[PDB]
Image (tube, rainbow, N blue to C red):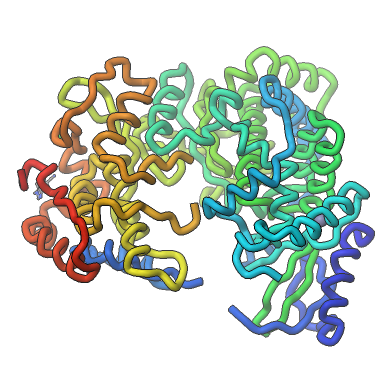
Length: 574
Ligand SMILES: N#Cc1ccc(Cn2cnc3ccccc32)cc1
Ligand SMILES: [Cl-]
Ligand SMILES: [Zn+2]
Ligand SMILES: [Zn+2]
């Protein structure tokens, strides 16, 4: 315990030797409080202006305006699972890893790969000012090289999480990425490799994936969201995930084993408390890993939980209190005989999941799931799961998927969500100190995503043409903080569409290109109203009629540049 974390604690305590104190009134129970030192400091979402000027009817929708404005979950403990549960998880984790690594090879990620990642402004939780300064400098990689040697010796000095999301100093992110980055970077959780997974599939393929699941014989499709899944990660899960190292070798295996046992399984965290003071607390369980590593581990553990719930549903094991030597061989024979087929009945994306089990016994297979700590959100603990009989209403990654027939007979499966949600997100700009040019480039990014993924929604196709028309044609799309983002490009969007939906799409057998935007269909007007369209309102009819005047107001605010008129792509203006 304190033989592992004590080293990190001493360093921070010594830096603030003139401000150290063990306060009497500390609110931590589940967290172990080690001490505190004095601090004083705090990101409030800002309005992307180009987007708001071109979506005026939504200035009065409070679903949209409210999004732009504006604890006791992390301070919770999970009961140690039963012995029978722990054995099932241990046996399944072991069999899963072996499957994931049949056609993979664990490997250390490089300083070159991590370097190019910070240059492209990748999303990472963090002497030097910017994230790019320490990478260019060499004295950093000495700080990294120091820790790296201490990790090989089985000790840790500077790998302390920051709670503001679990941030960490860039050096720790590198060492984390070096050992475990291979899971993301070499697509371990691809659908080709993992069967349940969807990493790097993109909003335009998920829909086709749910449908392919649907085509299998079985019961309802079950989409149960776990209540605060990161805070429901047990130490037994952290141990089951660490069994990946058993597929590694040499310097890699020891560097991985280190991260797991020194950072994940023994955490140290600095937390600001307004009463301002920085409290140094520790804990062994819960999730705080790298946002990208977390995804792959959450997908791993979630696959494991869902495979076990299917075994409970199919009556492979009777009771979780203790596992018999006949219940072991049966569970093991199950994984070997059908475990692959049962993975292909799922779509898992981190804490998210959609399962089409063999029958509806699954719905009331809640003993193992509740014991693993994977407690379902907003349903009684022992009340059975409400199934879905139609794949076009099943929720997945914040979306639902409409089947949609093109005028030449070919079948698009398009993603969709409440249009008040899409317009509200586009109107937000994360960060301060943005130029009119930068804000405008982010707007083009959303409009190009809308034209590619949400083209079938009338108000988005129109507002997309308007935004692209109000932004100089060459000005490149920019991202605030980084699956597949093909809308990030200056190429002609009808050409992107043809590549994405016709050329590259393996569910389309006829590869005849689409020649104009009119050949690309919309959802029914009621479907479009059901998913939140304003078609039929006077405001939207006025907005659409007088659309050029808004484009010209933005054109006037930016200045005299090279602008294109994209509105003639729609029939009404044509
Ligand atoms: N269900 C339904 C419904 C039927 C008609 C309208 C009127 N409306 C206004 N703008 C439109 C654009 C394209 C199509 C219709 C449009 C609204 C909703
Ligand atoms: Cl219709
Ligand atoms: Zn360390
Ligand atoms: Zn919809």
